[PDB]
Structures are given as C-alpha cells and as structure tokens.
Length: 264
Length: 265
Ligand SMILES: [Cl-]
Ligand SMILES: [Cl-]
Ligand SMILES: [Cl-]
Ligand SMILES: [Cl-]
Ligand SMILES: [Cl-]
Ligand SMILES: [Cl-]
Ligand SMILES: [Cl-]
Ligand SMILES: [Cl-]
Ligand SMILES: [Mg+2]
Ligand SMILES: [Mg+2]
Image (cartoon, rainbow over the protein chains, first blue to last red):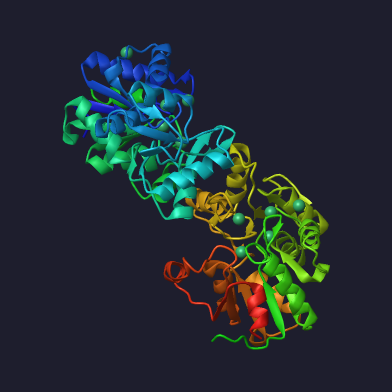
C-alpha cells in the first residue's frame, strides 16, 4: 500500500527545512507533490512567527506557496479568537510574531485585568511579572487559549522549553488547563487544515518528523500518517521513539522525496 | 476551645503573624515577647526561598525582637543543610536567588552548571528567565536528585497573588514528568521535623501557629501537633469559613493574633 491521497498536511520543521535552511530532499518532495496536482497545506506549531514570515521562508527554499497553503499556530490562534469574538481584548504571554497576527485579525492587545482572552504563546523574554499577569488572568476565569502544547522544543544544542512550560506552570498554580489548544496534535489546527483543504481525513495524509506531534495529530483526525526521518526521528532512534510515544506511523520514509517516489 | 493549653514549644510562621514583608505586626511582635517571658521554646519557621537566615534574623531584630540563630528555620537554610547532610560538599545547580545561593555556599555546597550538578535545587526567582529555565529543564532531564525549597503555588503578596516556587515545580513537572524528590518547606514534614529536632520536643508538646490553613495548619497536622490559626494575615474573620472550606482543614484554635493566643493561656 502507498500513501496516495488527494491532499497532504505537511509539517515544516524537520521535513522541508530546519530553521532557515532547506532540507534538500524535503523541498524536492514538495515540488514533485505539487507537480502531481496534489493539494498541500503546510501546518506549523510555531508560536513566535507570523504567516508572512513563514511564507517568505518557504519561498526562500525555492517553493511556490500561497497564503492559503500555510496554517501556522500564530495565525490560527488569532483567527480562532476573531471568529468567536471580533475585536476581542487579549492579554498574551507571547512574542512579536504572535502579536502581529493578533493585531492583523482585528484583536486588541491589553493587560490581564482588561482582557477577555488569555493567550499563551512561548516567549524567549518570558519573566516573573508576565507570569504574574498570566496567573491573575487565569484566576479571573477568562477564556484561555494556547498557541501550541509542545513541552520541549528540540533544538541543536539540546532541549529547550516549549509553550508547554507556561501551560504547565499555570496548570500547577491554578488547576486550569487551556480551554483551547490550537497547535498539533490538537484537533483544532488539524480540522481547520481539513477545512482549508476541503477534504475529509480519509483523503489526506499527515506528514511529519515527530511521532508525539505529527503522527498523533494524524491519529486524532483519522488520517493516514507518514513519518519522515529528516528531523527529530532518525533510523537510530525510531524504535525507541515508537516505544516512548506509544504510536506507530502508517508509513516511514527517509525523506519526503522517498514518500513521493513511492507513489509511482 | 476558647482557652489555649500550655505547650512547651511553638513553631511560629513569620509572614502574616509577626510581620508582613518588612513591616511588623505589633500584636504578633508583642505575642512573641510574652511567650519568651513565659519561658516557652520558640522557633520561627519560614518558607521564604529567597532570603538568607542572616537577612531574616536582621528583619526580626528590626521588629525589636531578641532572637538567636537557632530560633529561625528558613527554607533556604533548611534546604542547604538537608543537602549537605546527605552529601557534604555536593555540587548543585539552582534556579534560586542570591539568598538561597548564600545558604547553599554557607553549607559548603558547590554551585555548578546543570551538566556537572549532583542536585537540582528549585527555589523561586524574581529574575527567572528562559535561559535559567532551559538550564533547569536540562538538569531535570538528567534525572539527578531534585530538591525544592518550598511547594507554594501562589504567594499571597500584599498587592495581589504572585507565583510561588511552585510555578517552577509546575513547569518542570509538565515538561519532564518529574516532581521534586524532596520538598523541604511547609507543609512538608521535612522542615517541620527539623524544627521539632531543634526544639528538642515531641509534637505532642508543640503548637504550630500560622495564617494559612493550607500551609501552617496542614504543616501541624502532618506532624501531629496542635494547630493555631491567627487572623493577622491571609485568613480573616470574614473569610475564615471560606478558607476552611477551600483548604479542607480545620485548625484546633483560632485567635485574632498571636497576642490573643498568649493571653488565652
Ligand atoms: Cl522560527
Ligand atoms: Cl515552523
Ligand atoms: Cl513549489
Ligand atoms: Cl513551542
Ligand atoms: Cl521577603
Ligand atoms: Cl519570611
Ligand atoms: Cl538574602
Ligand atoms: Cl514562594
Ligand atoms: Mg517538525
Ligand atoms: Mg504566613
């Protein structure tokens, strides 16, 4: 059996690029998928970059990509809120790229005492007072959205905290988890992706480099899952990752290029 | 019971009882003076993870109290000595502030980076940042022995709730699945049994006095000591029933202030 579908939900980091640098076989793979006429949407959990920046990044990899072909957690979070409550007042722990999207969606950036929504995103400049403000917003009982649940972001010099750090802190202090988690493996971003694709899950494959994020995301919407080995998961650690995370992908390929070549 | 039975010793919380931050509570200060005149053994037990024993001694003396080193057991000191006893000169990595670092050094411990540490020591830090949390994460992931100064999730500061040391505990648990191996501060038995061992008294002869049901009353219950709640701090006459209900525990005695407890003997 081959992973031959009408549409593809494709993770960026570890599949198509690593930070600002392209993964050559990932790029080749996406180009050939596009040439075959498949519908593609890139889905990213990035909580600090705007849709604009990631579109520019993909184009710098040599890809032809339109606005509708990228769904990033910053944008998806802002949108989600704007649909619920146009011009909502939001207090955020997050960074400029998230703030950019919140503003583009018509939302008003305010302090915790004025907020209608608490929006948790990662912040490299997080500090004790921002955490105090988030704590108090939490205790006010206002609607609480998180951009993505990632506990640990796998970086080259080692693990660093993800948005999950703030989520964890707030849960421990108040007993409150987010009302809504947007990013993978949440169904929120995934179902929005299906919507944008205009396809049901049976006609979609979800492609990524993390079993706990991408494969779990596919499982959550009942789409077939493809794990590539160009990112976090390797030939060396594959069996251990399957064990650690408790899920097996439907397919494993060295890179996206190999997945596409399996369609011929 | 409106009257207080005569205990040989007292474990007394500071914040909300004797002072609020650097400001004395006159009825608390007077209560301590009177207990000392009665010849009762006293130890102040504080969950403060940012201040050294040196600084809290100075603070109590600034309230006009005559207090010795052995009469204060603060979580910074208690944590450092707990570790040093287990492993003299242990290498430690900490998230804490200068006050904790001071006590760790005074106990003979070596402050090192996360990759060399034998213990992870979690204390609150008002200058907490992403780099420090990265370091803590990595120390935590190594599986090394992990001690927390105190478990307080929320610290009841004068101008509204602020995060406690439990913020960092919470973050690390969520990211790694690990809770501290040992929690030192109240309501943990660790600091409380050390207090009993400084007093040279069994719990049956000691009352534990504080302003928080979830910390001070819980602490006394954990060692089987009678509990006294004063109303000079977090708990008030107005919110008392709400606090019993929220925290799920009843103190043995309630007095408006430490002075009133002492007068009821
Ligand atoms: Cl980035
Ligand atoms: Cl990304
Ligand atoms: Cl392209
Ligand atoms: Cl993240
Ligand atoms: Cl203080
Ligand atoms: Cl204190
Ligand atoms: Cl200090
Ligand atoms: Cl604290
Ligand atoms: Mg990835
Ligand atoms: Mg207190």
